[PDB]
Amino acid sequence: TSPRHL
Amino acid sequence: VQLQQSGAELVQPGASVKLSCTASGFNIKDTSMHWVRQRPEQGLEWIGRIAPANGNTKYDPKFQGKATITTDTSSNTAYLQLSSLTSEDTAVYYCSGSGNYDWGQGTTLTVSSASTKGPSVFPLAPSSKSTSGGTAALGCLVKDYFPEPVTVSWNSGALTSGVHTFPAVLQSSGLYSLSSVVTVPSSSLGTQTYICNVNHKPSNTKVDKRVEPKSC
Amino acid sequence: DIQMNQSPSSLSASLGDTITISCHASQNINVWLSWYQQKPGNIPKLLIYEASTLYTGVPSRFSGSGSGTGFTLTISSLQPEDIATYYCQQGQSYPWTFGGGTKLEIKRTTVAAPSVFIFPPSDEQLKSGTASVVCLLNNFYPREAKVQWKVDNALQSGNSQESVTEQDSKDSTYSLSSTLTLSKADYEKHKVYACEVTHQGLSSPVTKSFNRGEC
């Protein structure tokens, strides 16, 4: 899974 | 940790550009790279992203097909390619990574048939009269350039308090102009030297100009 | 896709107040919602992610909360450093979508008078054929200001442009710079150049003038 914000 | 993005581009309508952003502080293969843009005086539009260790890609429907995102893992950079550039696509394109990293500095793309022109930097000399409070205004006038971003700093980023750089105005000639002023103690007009650092990447114009009280 | 309805689009409030920006989602996004702050004028910086998890370095006066489809960014003790536009961003599914944005302005209680300066054109510019004078109005609080040019008591109209900064992050004021552009021939034919500025904080219009050839 990858991060969900910049 | 910081990202540097390519200089502000000028390109003709219907053409294609390839914007880049390099990473220094982390590995490209170690996170996802995202592109977002911001039209002048508008909100934020998410363009797409490329997965770490390429890796699949995802895009936004309005950029589907007209935008491709790729990475050069050896160079530790990321790219955004846009085609069929219309006058709607002139914006500031940000590049950033998933996680707590900062965003890219930003690349301003301008889609226009006009030609690049470099600016001329003029001094706004503080007047000989020294009014109350011990304050005196001095500045730089940046005139006749295209396309936009001209970035102005004072003393290479040292001088910050009292600095006002105004938004650019559009002259009848099709060339932009903006001013940058700073309030300063009158007792230091001859002692402290004040430099304004003007950058204009599309024309490769890098100028530092000293403002100095005119001698009479 | 998932649309983020951010509200209000613009909000003005006095110093020290408490502020709530809300962001409604078209679908359920669990807690995968973030907040960003964009001061004028630099890059957007992350304030809060995962609806409520603060980011290291963000002042404690920012707080976030919400789940599912309802979210709220709370700004207690409103400080002038909070002049910026705020966006909510969801990351539950692709394509990621931002909110419309929220322009936050400080409602300063006291009127501030502008300091007026005038600048003659540089002799370096007079070699090019044009001569542009500049009138500075910095640090005043009401945005409404009026600038008029008089070249030898002749009201100049149509040949000047103006620009205004955003709210200063220190005293919550504005700044204005007006550029009057003349040809070199026109500049050398007249002596007196004035800048008459009317304003709510002045009680009487002020005029900074200069004659060409003083220095």
Image (tube, coloured by chain):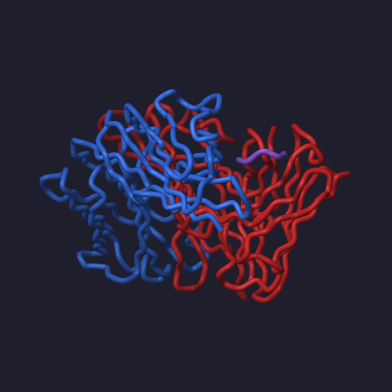
Residue B178 to residue B117: above or below: above
Query: Where is residue C86 drawn, in percent x and y?
Result: 44, 43
Indicate the quadrant where residue C81 lies. Answer: top left
Task: Name the tint of chain B in the rendering.
Answer: red
Residue B216 in view, yes or no: no
**What residue do we see at 32% from left, 27% from top?**
C77
**What residue do we see at 75% from left, 56% from top?**
B69
Which image quarter is the N terminus of chain C in? bottom right
Tell me, by letter, which chain the rendering colours blue: C
Task: Name the tint of chain A in the rendering.
Answer: purple
Viewer-proximal residue among C62 and C92 = C92
Indicate the quadrant where residue C74 lies. Answer: top left
Viewer-proximal residue among C55 and C152 = C55
Residue C112 to residue B108: above or below: above
Query: Where is residue C75 drawn, in percent x and y?
Result: 37, 32
Q: Is residue B119 left or right of residue B178?
A: right
Query: Where is residue C115 drawn, in percent x and y?
Result: 27, 41
Q: Residue furthest right?
A: B74
Residue C21 in view, yes or no: yes
Viewer-proximal residue among B178 and C77 = C77
Total numbered labels: 0
Q: Is residue C201 left or right of residue B194?
A: left
Query: Where is residue B77 drawn, in percent x and y?
Result: 79, 46
